[PDB]
Picture 1 (tube, each protein chain N blue to C red):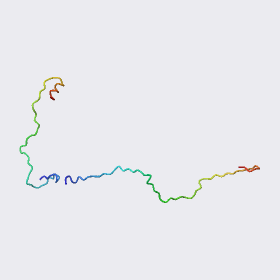
Picture 2 (cartoon, rainbow over the protein chains, first blue to last red):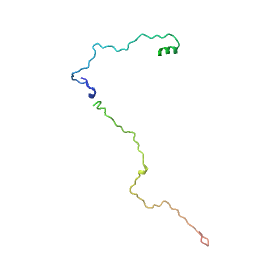
Picture 3 (cartoon, helix red, strand yellow):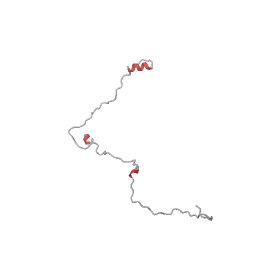
Picture 4 (cartoon, chains in turn green, purple):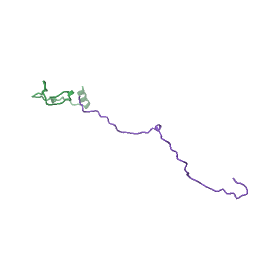
Length: 53
Length: 53
């Protein structure tokens, strides 16, 4: 059993009426990679302007 | 209690000692007897016929 902050978070052998649980088939939380945003060729400032607007 | 055992510590260091002249006190004053430091002797000779000063 795991105890609360008042108990200083102690983990001790025991039992309780509730229980922390974890997915048996966890999902990856990796950040998806999206399709690239293509900016037309141009001057540096123009490209930045198109990006930030 | 939470994090009991992480007791606060009070550290003393960097001691320095000034001096207060106005705090002066003295005990019994002892004065010694007069002691002869030095002596010079001489002769004043008058072989004339009148007193000389």
